[PDB]
Image (cartoon, coloured by chain):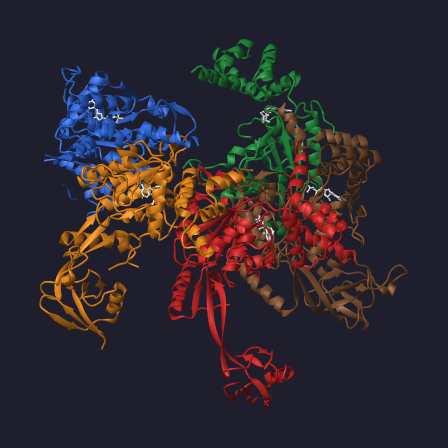
Chain colours: A brown, B orange, C red, D blue, E green
Amino acid sequence: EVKSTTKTQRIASHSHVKGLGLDESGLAKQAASGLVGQENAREACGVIVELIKSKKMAGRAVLLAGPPGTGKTALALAIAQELGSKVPFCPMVGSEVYSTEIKKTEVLMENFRRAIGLRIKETKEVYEGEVTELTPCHVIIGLKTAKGTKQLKLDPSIFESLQKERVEAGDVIYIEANSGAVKRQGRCDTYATEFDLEAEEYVPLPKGDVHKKKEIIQDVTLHDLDVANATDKLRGEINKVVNKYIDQGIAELVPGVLFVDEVHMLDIECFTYLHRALESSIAPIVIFASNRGNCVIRGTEDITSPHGIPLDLLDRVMIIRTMLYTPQEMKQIIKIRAQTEGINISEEALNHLGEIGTKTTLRYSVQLLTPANLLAKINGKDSIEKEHVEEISELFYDAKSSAKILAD
Amino acid sequence: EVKSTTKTQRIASHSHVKGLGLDESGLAKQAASGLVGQENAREACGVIVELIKSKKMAGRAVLLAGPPGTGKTALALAIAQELGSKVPFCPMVGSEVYSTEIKKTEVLMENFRRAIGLRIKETKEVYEGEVTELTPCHVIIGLKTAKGTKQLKLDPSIFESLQKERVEAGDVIYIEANSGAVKRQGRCDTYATEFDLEAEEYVPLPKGDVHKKKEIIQDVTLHDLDVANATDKLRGEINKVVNKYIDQGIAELVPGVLFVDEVHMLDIECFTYLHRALESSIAPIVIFASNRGNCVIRGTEDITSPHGIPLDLLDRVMIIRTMLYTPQEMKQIIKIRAQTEGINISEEALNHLGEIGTKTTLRYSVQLLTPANLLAKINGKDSIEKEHVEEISELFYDAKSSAKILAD
Amino acid sequence: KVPEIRIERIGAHSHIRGLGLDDALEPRQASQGMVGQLAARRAAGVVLEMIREGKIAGRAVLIAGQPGTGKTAIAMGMAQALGPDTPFTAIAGSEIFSLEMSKTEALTQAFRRSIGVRIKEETEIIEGEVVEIQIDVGKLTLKTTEMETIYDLGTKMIESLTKDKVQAGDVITIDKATGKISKCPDGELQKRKEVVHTVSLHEIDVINSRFLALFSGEIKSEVREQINAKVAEWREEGKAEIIPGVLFIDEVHMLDIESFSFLNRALESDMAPVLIMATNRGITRIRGTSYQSPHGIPIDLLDRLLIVSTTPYSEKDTKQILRIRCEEEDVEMSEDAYTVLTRIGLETSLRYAIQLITAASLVCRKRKGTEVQVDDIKRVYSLFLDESRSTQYMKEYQDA
Amino acid sequence: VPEIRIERIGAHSHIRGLGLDDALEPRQASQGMVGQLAARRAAGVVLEMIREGKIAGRAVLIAGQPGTGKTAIAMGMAQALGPDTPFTAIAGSEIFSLEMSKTEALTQAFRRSIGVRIKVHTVSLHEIDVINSRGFLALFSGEIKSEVREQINAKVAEWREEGKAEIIPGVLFIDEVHMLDIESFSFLNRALESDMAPVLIMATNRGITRIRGTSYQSPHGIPIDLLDRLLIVSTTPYSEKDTKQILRIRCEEEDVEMSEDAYTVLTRIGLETSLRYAIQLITAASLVCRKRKGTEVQVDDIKRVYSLFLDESRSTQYMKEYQDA
Amino acid sequence: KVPEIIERIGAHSHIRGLGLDDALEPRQASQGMVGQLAARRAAGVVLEMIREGKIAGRAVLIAGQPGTGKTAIAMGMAQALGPDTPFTAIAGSEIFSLEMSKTEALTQAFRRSIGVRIKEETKEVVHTVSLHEIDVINSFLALFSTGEIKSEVREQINAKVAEWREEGKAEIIPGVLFIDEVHMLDIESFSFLNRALESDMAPVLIMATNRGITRIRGTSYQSPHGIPIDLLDRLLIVSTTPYSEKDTKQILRIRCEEEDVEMSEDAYTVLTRIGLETSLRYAIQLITAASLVCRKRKGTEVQVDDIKRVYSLFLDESRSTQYMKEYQDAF
Ligand SMILES: Nc1ncnc2c1ncn2[C@@H]1O[C@H](COP(=O)(O)OP(=O)(O)O)[C@@H](O)[C@H]1O
Ligand SMILES: Nc1ncnc2c1ncn2[C@@H]1O[C@H](COP(=O)(O)OP(=O)(O)O)[C@@H](O)[C@H]1O
Ligand SMILES: Nc1ncnc2c1ncn2[C@@H]1O[C@H](COP(=O)(O)OP(=O)(O)O)[C@@H](O)[C@H]1O
Ligand SMILES: Nc1ncnc2c1ncn2[C@@H]1O[C@H](COP(=O)(O)OP(=O)(O)O)[C@@H](O)[C@H]1O
Ligand SMILES: Nc1ncnc2c1ncn2[C@@H]1O[C@H](COP(=O)(O)OP(=O)(O)O)[C@@H](O)[C@H]1O
C-alpha cells in the first residue's frame, strides 16, 4: 500500500531493544532483549504494560524522571515493543512545538497521529508458495503450493525485489497477485533440516492453491495516511474512511506510545491540549521524560511545579525514576551498541570508553564509536584500540567541557 | 415603556440610605436618612451636591479615599439620591474594563450610558379616579370622579395589575387609557383624617372626569434604550431619538453619579477616556474610590502616582477622606442592616458582631447575617443569638484569616 | 430541529452520595460515604440551606486548604445533596488556556455544562397482565384495573414475551423493552412514565452541532442563540425545567484578572449555577496584574465569597477513606497493609496512596494472590514514586 | 467646505500676555503675570526669536516644580504673539487614547495650532476639519478621515493663493512631556520640519528619567536628538507675596470677596501644598459662606473647607500609613 | 519555462583545502592553513564522515575565542570536499530581516547551501550552481528598491530538480552551511534546523560560537553555547586554541602576499604583536591602511612608522569601547 513516515534517525540509536525482558514472575534478569541493568524501572515499566493490557490506564500517564543518558527513551521504546508486534512509537521533544511556520496545534496533532496505529487485515488470493525454479525472461517462475508447481509471469522489477529480499530456491514467500510484490516470510519445509521446524522461520507447503487465501496484516499509522494523499479536510476524510474500515471489520485500532522528552519546554496551553487528548477511549500511552526539577511553567510567571508540569495533569501521572548506570553496566551497554553497529572494539578500549561514559554521559560515548572506527580504518586497522579512543576523545568534546573551556 | 437593567445586587447592600442626612445649615446629624457616622465626609458630600446643583462641577471629579468597608459606596449612593428623586447610580469596579469579548471602550461607554438618565414627561390619556365597584361580567369597572361614576370595560391584564397593586373599593388610583396599567396612588379622601392629606398617600376625588390628559413623569436610562433595540448604529438612532425628544421640550436628560471602586486597576488608557468624558457639558459626576496610596499607573512600568491616577486628571479631583467606625457606630450599622433585611437580632449578638467587625471589616460582618439567620431558623429559633453568630463565625472565614492559615 | 440524547468516568468520587450531615445541619461521623472534616461539611450544609432558600445569588463558595484534604469531595457532596440529578462540572483553573478555544469559549462551555435542563418526556407505557399470549403479527390481550384492551404487536416481540416472566410483569414501554417485575399493572391500561432525564446545555450544543473526531471545539454563535431561545420556549410551554447545577474550579489562582471579570458578569444572572472555587495558595499575585491579593482573587469578587476551610486528615480518617476506596475498587486488603498504606498517605499524600491501590492490586494478581499484602504495597511503593521523593532525589542530582 | 480647553475651564483667563515690555524688561505687576521675572524674560526672548524668524527647527522647554506657572508662561507667550493666535494645551497622557493612535492624536494636536484668518474670524485648522465631517452628545457618539484633510489642505493652499485667508502659526503646549515615548518624539521631530509648523513648548517636572519605550535614561525623558535643539527655561518656586497676589487676582476674576486674614491663611496653605489646591479651595469656601448667609469669606470658612477636602500629600500619606497593617 | 545561469571580500582567498592530508595527519605548513593541529585533525575526521555517508543526523560545532579561524576551518573543509562544493557562511543575526521571516531566511540559506551540476553537451561542460541561484533566476537597485521567494517557484524547482536527477544529466552535491555566532539563534529557529537536518539531501551543518553557558534565546533556561539539548547531543564539538606568535606571523605573511603588500621584518613583528593582544583580524584590517599610507609618501615598502601612524589613526575594538565606557562613567 503505502510507505512508512517514521523518523528512523531517532530510533536507530535504540536498535538493540527487543522488549523489556522480564520472566514469568516479573523479576528483572538484568540482561535480556538488549536492555541491561536498571531493574527497578524495567519492573515498573512491565507493571505499566500490564495496566495498559487490562485497560486500567483510563487517563493516567507515565513520567520518567532521571539524568540524561539513563535509558528513558530506551525504556519507552521497550514498552512500545512489549505492547505488541509493531505498536507504533513516536519520540519527540517539547522544543518542536515552537515552530515559526506551523502552529503548536499542528505539531501536537501530527505527533499524536504518529503514535496510534492501524492494523489492516484482509484475506487475499496471493501467490504464497515456494520458489522452485526461476527463469528470468517474462520472468517465468515456478511456485509450488499444496496444488503443485505453477508457472507465473512476473516483471523484472519483481525479480529485482526478490534479489533485494535475498531469496533462494526453497523459500515460502507471497508475491502479490493484484499488483506484484515480494516480501520475505521464511523458507520452505520441503527442504527443512532437523533444527528447522514448521510454523516458524521455515513454513510448510502453503495450503490451498497458488492463489492462496492468506490473511495479510499490514501495520500503518494515520500519519502515513495523511501523507499518502499527495488541511483539516484531508484529516477529516481519512477520519471517515478509517471509521468505515473499522465498522467493516477488516481494521483494528491499536494505541501506540507517544514519548515526550524535555517536558518542561511545553507551554501550559500544550499541557491542556495533552490533557484533552488523554481523555479519549483511543489514545497513546503518553510517556513524559524530565530532567529539570521544580520549574517555572512556560506561559506563566513566578509559578513553580514539579518537573515543569501543571498540577492539573501531573496528578494523573505515575513517576518512575531511572538511576545512573554503573561502569560495569556502562561497558555492557556500550558493547551491545558496538556489536549492533558492527564496530569491533577491544577490551581496554571498552574500559576507557566506560570511564568516559561515567565521566560525562552515555549518549556522548555512543556517538564516540563511529569516529573511533573511522580513525582506526584510516590508520590501516580493523579494530579500535585504546590509543585510538584516547585520540578521538581528545579531538572531540562534549557540551559541558567545551563550555567550561570557553568560559576561561 | 422599557424595563430596567440596573444591577440590583450591587445596590442591595445599600438600601436603607435615603439621602445625606444633612440639616438646613449643612451640618450632619449623628443618624438620619439611613446613615450613621462619618459626619465630616457627609458634610463634604453635601458641599459637593451644592456645587453640582450650582453648575460648579464643570469638568471636575470626586475621589473617596478610605480603607475598605467605610461607607464609600454608601456615600456615593447618598449623593446620587440627594441629587434628585431618581438620579441614576452606576457602580463599577475597574477590573471589569478587562473583558475578552467587548473592548475597554465598550465597557466604559456602557457604564457611562448607565448614569446619563432621562426624565420623560409624556402627555397621555389617563383614568385617575376612585375604583367604586368591580363587577366581573371583561370585568366592567366603575370609576368615580367629580363628574360621577363611569362604567368601562377593563382588560384582564389591567385587572391583574390592579390586584397586584392591592386596590379595593374606595381607592382613588390611576389607570392608563391608551396602553393600560394601574399604579396605586392612594385612597379617597372620604376617610381623610388629620394625617391623611390631599395629593399624597391619600388622593381626593379627581376634579374633571375619569378621562384626563396627564403629564406622566418616568425615569429611564440611555443604556435602557440600548437594551430596547434588540453596535454603534443602534446607539446613533438612540441619540437621534433623544435629540428629537429634548428639542420637543417634553423631557430632560439628567446627569447621574458614576462610581468607580478600585480606581488603581484602570489603565492609563482608560483614564484618558474618563478625562475626555467628564469634561463634556452633559456628563455624570464621576466619583472614584481608592484604598491604596502611591501606586504604579497600570500601562506604564515605573511611573508611580497618587492612587494610581495620572497627574493630569488628578489635578481636577477633590479628595474626601472616609474614616473607620467605632464599635457603637458598627453596632448601629449592623442593626440598621438587620432591620432592613427583616432579621431580628439580640443585643449581645450585636455586640459580638460588632467585635467581629472591628476585628476584620464591616462588609464581612454585614454578609454574616443571612447565614446566621438560616442557621437560627434551622435550629428552631426566631431571632439570632450569640451562639449562632459565634458558630457562623467559626464556620465561614474571611480572606485575611484564610490566607494566614494557608500561609503554613 | 433540535436533537437531544468526566469525574464519574474516572470514578474518584463514586462513593460520595450527598453531604451526609443531615440531622438538621449536624454532621454525622460516618454519614453517606464521607468521614471526618466536620466543620467544612457543616459549612457546606449551611451553603445548601442558603441555595435552597434562594439567598445565594450574587455570592459564591471558596474552599481553602492543603491538597489531598477533600475540596472536590465537599463540592461533590454539596452537588449531590442539592439534587439527585444536579449537574456538576469540576474543571481546573489551568484548563481554560487552550490552543483551540479562547478563554471566553472555555469558560462559557464550563458554565453552560453546569446548568441543566430536566427534559420530562411522558412516554406512553403499556402495562398489563398477559392473561393469554395472542398469536401473533396480531394483537395482545392486556388487562389492568381499568379494562382489557388488545394492542397490536409484532411476532418477534411475542416470541420475546413468551420467554419473559408470564404473567408476572410484562410492563412494556412503547416500542421499547418489556419490563418483567410482577403483576406494575394497575390503574389505567395506558400509563404515562414521565422520564425526567437531565442534561446540561453543552451536550445540547455538541449534539445540535458537529469516535476519533476528538483527535481531528468552538461552538458557533448561531447554535447558542437558537438553543438559548428554544430552551426558554420549552420552559414557557412546560416540557422541561431549568435546574441550577454546580460549577467547580480547582486551583482558582491559575485564573487571571481577564477572566474573573467574565465570572462576575456571568454569575450575576437568574439561571446562574452555584460557583465553587478551590485553592491551596495563600496571598499570591493576581495573574495579569502586579498587585497581590489573598488566594489570587481580586478584592471586588472576594468580598462576595463564603470561605470554608478544610483541615488536614488524621490517622483514623485516612484509614477510613482508604477502606472506602478499596471497597469501591474491588480490592481486598489486610490490616497491617492498611496501616502501612495509611502511614504512607499521611507521610506524603492521600492522592498518591489512592494511586498505589491499583498498582498493588495488579502486582498481587500477577502472583496469583487474592488479598493484597504488605509486601505488595512495599513493592509498588518502591516502583512508583511521589512528588516529593522524585523532586528531592533528582534535585540532589541537579546540585552538580 | 463649511466654515464658522484652558479658556473654558478657566484658571488662566486673567493672564493677558507676559506683560514684561519696556524692551524686554519684566514688569512686576504687568498684564496679570506675577513674579518669575527670569522665566518671563527668557520667554520674551523666545517671542523675539519667533517674530524675527529664528525659531525654525527649534523648540522651547519649561522645567520646574508643579504649580509654578509653566502653563501660565505658555499662555502668556501665546497672547503676546498676537490677539487671536491658536494655543493648544495638551498633556503627555492624552496621546494614549482608545480611539485614536498616537499618530492621529498628535496630528490633531498639531492642526489645532495652525490658525486661519478669514476676512476677521480666526479658526483652527482642525476645527475646520471637524466642521467638514458630518446629537447633543456627539462627544460620546475620532479618526476624522484621511482624504478630507488632504482636500482641506489643498483648499487652504488655494485660499492662500487668491488672498481670502491668512495662515497664523500658533503655539502647541505639551504638559508632562516625559509621558511621551520614543515613538511620539520621532513624530514630533519629523513634524517640526515644515513651513507651516507651530511653535512647540514642552513642560516637565522631572529630572533624569528613563525614556519611555527604551532602556536608557536621559534628562527629562527626552531623546538626545530633540534635547540638543531645545531652549530650556527654568521656573523657580513662588514665594509668599507672589502667591498672595495670584490668589487676589484669581478671586477678583471669579467674583469672590475675601478678608485679609483669610487671604494670608490661604496663601500659607497654598505655599505648603500647591497653588492649584489653594485655588480649588476658593470656590468651595465661597459656596460654604453662601449657605451661612455670609457675604465675606472668613477664616473659619477656610478652616471648614480645609478640613472637608484633602490635599494630595495628606491623602496619599494617610493610606500609605494605612497599609502598615 | 525554466532557465539556468566570503569570496567577494576575499578574507579567505588563501584557503585551498584543509591541508592535513597524509592519511589524517596535520601538516604544519600544508596549503594555506597554519597551526591548530587538533582542529585540523578533527575536521578531517568529520570530512571522512561526510565522504562515506555517516554524518546524516549529525552536525559540527566549533567553539573558540574570536580570531582563531573557525570560519577558515569551515572554508577548508568545504574546499576539500571538492572544487565545486557550495559553501554558505551566514551569521546568526542575519536571520532577523525586515522583509524575510526566519522561515524564509533559513530556507534560503539551506537551499543556497545545496549545489547541482549541469552537464551541457555542445563536450559536456559542467557548471555547478546552487539551488537558490536557480530560484532567484525565476523571479540594478534590486538589492535596495522584497526578496521573498514565492512557494510555487520553490515546488516547481524541486519537481524540476527531481526530474533532471532521474533523467541522468544533473547530480546533487550537498554543500556546507556555516552559521557564525550560533548563540544568537532562538528556539524557534533551532527547531527549524533540527527538522531540516532530517532530510536525505541535507547539507553539512557547521555552527560556530565564542560564548559559553548562555540563556537560550526565546526561553529562560541556561544551556551550554545557547543551543537546546535536543540538538546538542547530535553535535561534534571541536575547539580552536588561540594562536601564538609564529603562527600569527605566518598568517600575516600569507595575507600580505595575498593582498599585494611588501612589509619589512620588524614591521611584521610589530603587526604580529598587534594581532597578539588585540586581535589578528584587526592587524589584517591594518595592513591595507598601512599600504595606502605608504603610497602617500611615495614608498614601495611599508615601514614600522607606517604601522605606528595607522594604529593611531584607526582604533581596535577594545580601546574604542573602553574610551566611551570610561567617559560615560566619568559623565
Ligand atoms: N538499561 C539500558 N539497556 C540498554 N541500553 C541502554 C540502557 N540505558 C541506555 N541505553 C542506551 O543508551 C543510548 C542513549 O539513549 P538514552 O539513554 O535513551 O538517552 P536519554 O537517557 O538521554 O534519553 C540509547 O541508544 C539506549 O539504547
Ligand atoms: N455611614 C453608613 N451608614 C449606613 N450604612 C453604611 C455606612 N457605611 C457603610 N454602610 C453599610 O455597610 C456596608 C459597607 O460596605 P461599603 O460601604 O460598600 O464598603 P466600601 O464603600 O469600602 O466598598 C455597606 O453595605 C453599607 O450599606
Ligand atoms: N471527608 C472525606 N470523606 C470521604 N472521602 C474523602 C474526604 N476527603 C477526601 N476524600 C477522598 O480523597 C480523595 C482525594 O481528595 P481530593 O478532594 O481529590 O483532594 P483535593 O482537595 O486536593 O482535590 C478523593 O477521591 C476523596 O474521595
Ligand atoms: N506668574 C504668574 N502669573 C499669573 N498666574 C500665575 C503665575 N504663576 C502661577 N500662576 C497661577 O497658578 C496656577 C497654577 O499654575 P500652573 O501653570 O497650573 O502650574 P503648572 O506649571 O504645574 O501647570 C494657575 O492657575 C496660574 O494662573
Ligand atoms: N589556521 C589558519 N590559516 C589561515 N588563516 C587563518 C587561520 N586562522 C585564522 N586565520 C585568519 O584569521 C581571520 C579570521 O578568521 P575567521 O574565522 O574568518 O574569523 P574569526 O576567527 O575572527 O571568527 C581569517 O581572515 C583567516 O584568514
Q: Is residue A287 visible?
A: no
Quarter containing the N terminus of chain D: top left
Residue C109 percent location from the top left of the image? 47, 56
Q: Quadrant of ligand 4?
A: top left
Compared across the picture, whether B63 is left or right of D264 comes to right
C17 and E130: which one is in front? C17
Measured along the vertical axis of the image, is residue E180 above or below residue B7?
above
Furthest residue in direction right, as rendered: A194
Q: Is residue D92 visible?
A: yes
Residue E60, quarter of the rendered image = top right
Compared across the picture, whether D200 is left or right of B212 comes to right
Measured along the vertical axis of the image, is residue A165 above or below residue E128?
below
A308 and C149: which one is in front? C149
Residue B376 percent location from the top left of the image? 44, 53
A16 and A369: which one is in front? A16
Quarter containing the C terminus of chain D: top left
- Marker count (numbered): 0
Residue C368, quarter of the rendered image = bottom right
Measured along the vertical axis of the image, is residue B231 above or below residue B309?
below
Compared across the picture, whether D44 is left or right of C228 comes to left
Give me the residue at 9% from left, 64% from top: B208
Residue E43 percent location from the top left of the image? 68, 32
